[PDB]
Length: 325
Length: 139
Length: 139
Length: 22
Image (tube, rainbow over all chains, first blue to last red; front, side):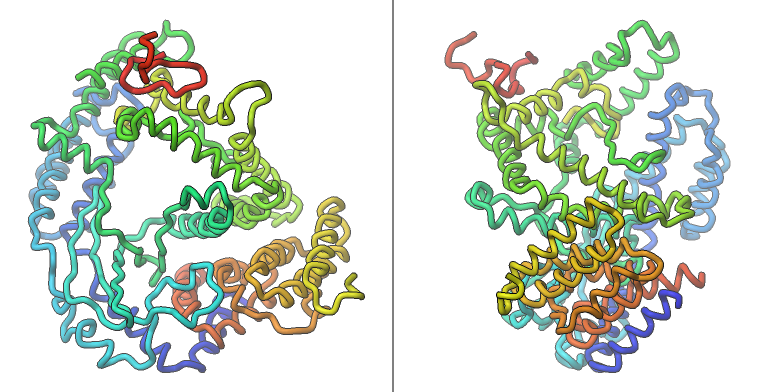
């Protein structure tokens, strides 16, 4: 029979036993899935950043298109117009259309406008009141009011079955949802930070990723393999004395597009450090890439040979100039 | 994975990411004393019996192969022999990479010389300048 | 030794490994693979000491190299006893993806047994899988 | 060269980032 028939049979067998537990888990999943979706501004930021990265990658792959005469090749205008029409709020559609669709620009103005829009949206998102009440993400607060007054069968904190244990007697149960929700913007995305209290006073933090990537299962498989490998390291002598372990957060999919990830609140990316230094020193974060693109365009428009095999000394000189400047 | 053939390939100028800024954050003394030795320690502890790593990697490689074949939309046979052969080949490649790092030299050379060679290759500016702009070889 | 021993699992594991190696060397001795699967099942049932996960991985690898007649998938009938589904929980993704490839009955038996004792280990993954199947098969 | 300096290079040692390169 089709796989979904067997899946439904297993689900029915599961529901016949533990009806109240299944009901509680289903209600919790439904509430999280319904009230933790992206607002329009974050969608706009995500899509603008994706378009800018794609344009930079294309120009890098095929230089000489960065000149002021190439008229937006690769049939990307279809993507531009589709994004303007069916993925943009009515409020900002006119300005976006006037800036992008009407002008029909070259690559230079394309990237310039994308950069301006990205900066605008970054500034807009960074000035939000970050800690938002948990009772706002609801119509009658089925998350702050639920759970110790609305649950049925003592749900467990998710993600505890991915570990290499021998019994579940001492698993931590959900006791409460903390009433504050953080707003976090990453380099190209953003999410909400939930927090849970266990029945022993411990606190666990998760990130809710609504537009989960297209390759989540592969990453989960890699994490599974290296979580398996951590046991041998824990049991071997040359490694256990140095305390060598891979760092692998727990991930639990709720829907084929939603996912919760165990969170560390003190993370920072290397890109963030670079951008903070640029901000403090009055520089521009985008200067090196524009410099590289312009120099490669100039040196490839002319002869692109006379260097030994592929280590074009022009590339090394550009790299040294970037390092020095 | 290579889009043409079912193999594990990187095809980048450097073996891994080790740029000048990370090197400066670590420092020369720490880079020599901790970073270089830990890689060999992990390799030695994981490849002690050589039949453990392959057994651990079998299912992961099988799933990767199934995904590749399904995405290429060119299975057309579900041939078990082909699956077995490809899985064995890929597991052998990965175990070769792991066993290279855990091997000591023959003469009077230091225990971790392959790791030092790899670090030299990854810090050479000649091939650090052939990376893409989004990779930011600087920093 | 298997005749002499009462409940020793090391003998079962060694016989299973020997039969598996014999099958690997000669890719036409299905009876050897069947014996290896049965021995692995016996050893896993006798261990209950967190060392049956490797045996379960070997069993899952064996099940995927079956013929059209399910010759390998008969050591389950050959072996009588409990399963101790606790040690299979780490492999739920493999079972869920395998219930659509030529071996649905065997993995489905284990999944059904898990559903009746550890619902919280399976609810979310099963729900996501069901949604995926609904989206793909009957878009 | 420069005895008792940790910035010297040697085929059996890592390069070091404070000198240009081997």
